[PDB]
Amino acid sequence: AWSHLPHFSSPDLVNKYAIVERLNFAYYLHNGRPSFAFGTFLVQELIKSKTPKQLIQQVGNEAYVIGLSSFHIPSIGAACVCFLELLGLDSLKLRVDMKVANIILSYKCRNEDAQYSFIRESVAEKLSKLADGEKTTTEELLVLLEEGTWNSIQQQEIKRLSSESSSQWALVVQFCRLHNMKLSISYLRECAKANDWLQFIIHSQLHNYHPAEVKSLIQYFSPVIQDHLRLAFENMTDLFEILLQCSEEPDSWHWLLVEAVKQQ
Amino acid sequence: DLKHFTEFAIGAFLRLLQEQLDEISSRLHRLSKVVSEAQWRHKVVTSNHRSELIPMMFSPPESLLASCILRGNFAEAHQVLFTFNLKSSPSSGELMFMERYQEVIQELAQVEHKIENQNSVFYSISDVTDKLLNTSGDPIPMLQEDFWISTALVAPLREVLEDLSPPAMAAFDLACSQCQLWKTCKQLLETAERRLNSSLERRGRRIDHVLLNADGIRGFPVVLQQISKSLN
């Protein structure tokens, strides 16, 4: 029963549908109004932030979402960085995301024929998927990163494993660590097949290659510079050996028998 | 049973509505007044949807102006501003900026490539800067510094806010708008630095550098100088 002559603002109906909104920080950020963005955000929310830690974390999550939304566009990325810095948090997650998406261009565009916008939509979907912590999708994304990185390295027309090679390759470790994924064996092998020790030493070192991986991948080099290496940092099937190394047991009467019962 | 059977409307229904209204013309004034604001809004609301329910069609004049700014279009919103029977919101200054800084950015964007090709200007860039920094007519609603403090309806972070530079609060923003040339970065930093110096002189306060913020502010001028020295 609409007794009162109602209009676009019938009081009872107006209450039934009073839905107001404030100029949320997305206005400035999405436009790109950095210092004003932070300042207006504080004006509206800092006092209003009855839960400063919780509200700050929520705003950071929003900032990360916003940034991830706009990989290609430059201005949005710069705004994201500035707002994160003014927020008071880390400035490496968003930058890592940006660098990864940017470097993924070459061997997705100069190798595949499609409209860049569909590629952008696919990349954004994959990015949101990664934000969900999709470990399998994370692995696929890093794999593509390696592939495109190899393509780009080749493009510059230099030796595939020189110094500047590692210089560009740093991001390979950077991403994997940043996303808490197992350090992928990227260039260690690529130098391992080529018999270049003074790269498997250094580049093993300056990222803290965990001691299992270096030894495990050591078995690719050569006949020579392989025995001088497996024993380098250590810390059978031959009767002249099974008995030579049988002077080590409790006495003997069980190592030989235990070894000989197993293999007939 | 009625339930058995259960913008184009914004045209069609309004058609016969105005048809009956004109036929009668050949309470009602109150009734017409209610429908007086519709078609333009109906257009504008359709213009709103076309830009991108009756819940969308019942936004408060504040929320109405909000949707008007949503797409970032000022010309269409101008009529809503004129006929909204209200002219009290910082969004007025926001429209000011959207109208001015837009062409400002276009001119700056051309100026950069022009400068490079000539090398293959600073005074004009500074003039474009002042075009936002200085207002020919009425002052920009954000042009006031304590206008930010005006937005404060009140704390521990008030002192943090005392580190703010509203005159630069958009200046650094615009420097990040699209500044994309070497000397262009140099100037877009140096002029904003002049603005910061003017802010401090207006501030009349010392640089409490050691004044670390417990709430989690990393330093407005501090971040500014961080970027400055990093560029250096």
Image (spheres, rainbow, N blue to C red):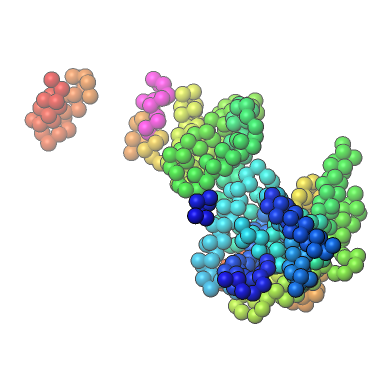
A216 in the magenta segment: yes
Residue range (magenta): A215-227
Query: Can I make out residue A194 in this image?
Result: yes
Q: Residue at x 12, y 29 (%)?
A: A258
Camera-nearest residue between A32 and B172: A32
Residue B186: image location, x then y, percent: 80, 53
Tell me which residue sits at (63%, 65%) in the image: A21
Residue drawn at x 85%, y 69% as measured from the top left: B139
| Residue B168 appears in the picture as rendered | no
In the image as oriented, which residue stretches furthest toward the bottom?
B154
In the image, residue A24 above or below residue A137: below
**Foreground of the two, A189 or B11:** B11
- Rendering coords of residue B101 (x, y %): 81, 56
Q: Is residue A217 left or right of residue B223?
A: left
For residue A18, what is the image quadrant? bottom right
Q: Is residue B173 magenta?
A: no
Total numbered circles: 0
Quarter assignment of residue B209: bottom right
Magenta: main secondary structure equals: loop
- Residue that appears at 75% across and 54% down: B15
Q: Viewed as shown, does residue A244 lie left or right of B144?
A: left
Nearest the viewer among B3 and A230 is B3
Residue A142 spot, x, y in % from top left = 50, 37
Q: Nearer the viewer, residue B118 or A60?
A: A60
Q: Taking A34 as reference, is A205 above or below it? A: above
Q: Residue furthest left?
A: A253
Whole-percent x, y for residue A65 in the image: 57, 52
Image quarter of residue B169: bottom right
